[PDB]
Length: 364
Ligand SMILES: Cc1ccccc1-c1ccc2nc(N)c(C[C@@H](C)C(=O)N[C@@H]3CCOC(C)(C)C3)cc2c1
Image (cartoon, rainbow, N blue to C red; front, side):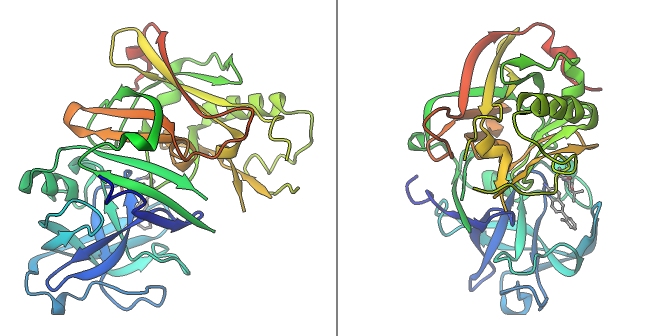
């Protein structure tokens, strides 16, 4: 798998992207890697922000599906025209697939000015695909049409350029230390998981574990922040505040809108999430450092409130090697060989723990 190591790039805050080709002859595009959506969508028109775009006129293997797609988001949108064509990943497996492609023809607040990517690879499941679940996502096509095992893994390394690896069809054991620990994919739409306990510096928040997963908890490479449900965020901050009241901060910094410049680190607590294990009454925990939730912009607060559920974004994923084990409906976490630490504390994955009533923690 050494051909796929270090195949991810990006700039701080503008997502991680992989190089892909579409059409024949191949057109090279940089494509955002997103485990929190399910469409393969690329710019197909000369939008000012774009370095390049999909030119369908130039592709002999392109087929029109004669159907449109409109994708609104909380802020802005994209829309396009559905079709299929041949796709490959230069620093991925040595295969070629016919996949669905949304050719983006109109967008609003989608593309980023100054970014170096031109599309998005939705790696989540068909149920959240637009317009509906009959548009087969790229990874489903890849597995169906080739002998690539139904599994991928992400080492997101962070920092200004960022780097990483998407190991398609397997695991590279050199990218983590210790052991992988697995949590069940609760249902195949998002990569939904169940959090069963939260600790701020060893201290249980003592909330009903249901609140951690209201109305869901997901693993999302397209989100920067650790995102927590409203009630949980307030409890969490009230706790991080108290744990680090040796220094003073405006109430807007936790919302979170100011810097701080030099580094102590040690006034801030570690954050531990306990995830449902593979075995009845068994859990494990993942622990992140302030290095993960204090993002340079001098730093900013990268935990924020949400009404979509818990979102385990880059803040979480940058501490760990993450295995999206689709074949066994599970997600693996191990300590990342590249995560940003100091000489006191490191990110951790630890188990097993005894946790009762873990099935009560999921929202219905
Ligand atoms: C930023 C944007 C602008 C216009 C249209 C779509 C988007 C967009 C694209 C990909 C996204 N990928 C993501 N992982 C996220 C965050 C996650 C938690 C999320 O809300 N995912 C939804 C999955 C279904 O499709 C949605 C509604 C566009 C995002 C938001 C996204 C928003």
